[PDB]
Image 1 (tube, rainbow, N blue to C red):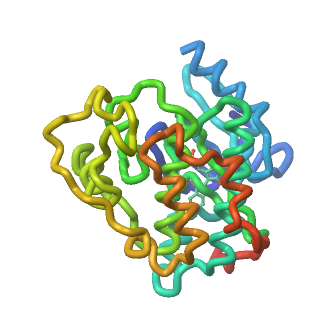
Image 2: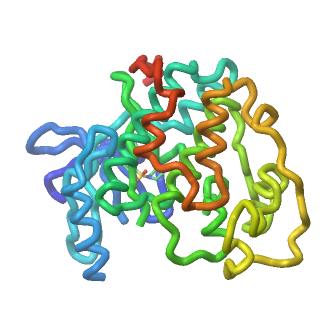
Image 3: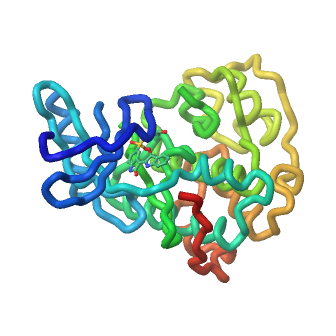
Length: 274
Ligand SMILES: C[C@@]1(O)/C(=C2/C(=O)Nc3ccc(S(=O)(=O)N4CCC(O)CC4)cc32)Nc2ccccc21
């Protein structure tokens, strides 16, 4: 801990306040987060989960009951990037690239049976080189929460990350959150008002979901042409497949990387204001 020099607070977090700090020894600029034997074993495992599209968990410093997560440092997050683009919007090639990289990150994690669980634009860090990385692998915002989690499912799968990335994908195209709920029922209902109240037809087993209510209003689905305009048919197809109620039928990241949409994928660089 005495190996670091906090240069300034750069954000916070459901766990802790993240600082920017240079390694007094190596000069290495990092993102210093200041946050249970299992909550140490688990977080140290991630240390071995290295992929280009996953922010690097350089180290973990549990000192004097104070936990510190020394992370690699990226200058900007997606939320502030999307904010800095609300007027023009992020170009489609950058949107495509990003989705593609995150999906490669997710594919890597998912292959290792590790889920993020809390995918948000603020956990997606970008750099001037054009990459995007999955920060803070999730150990107060429901906008991007998959419906199985809202319906009380306790053993939700990797498919939840996909739904979030779907919602995030939509938000980058639309410059507006897809399902901004202020409560869990409002979150669920907004999803309902768009994708149609789920039922045994489109989602076998939904009716047995812990928090499922036979009394849920019955909203009819709406076309994605109205959901994510002006996203082309390729993207809307991928989105709908990422936003499928039935988790089992929800497309995987691995499969998503092979969607015709990613045919013309490139690696454009953003124009960061640092
Ligand atoms: C997200 C971050 O705080 C940040 C971090 C970084 O470079 N590596 C990190 C690794 C993890 C997290 S976090 O996803 O654990 N976290 C804290 C910030 C919050 O808004 C979301 C959750 C923050 C950062 N750099 C910058 C720079 C400008 C905006 C936000 C940030």
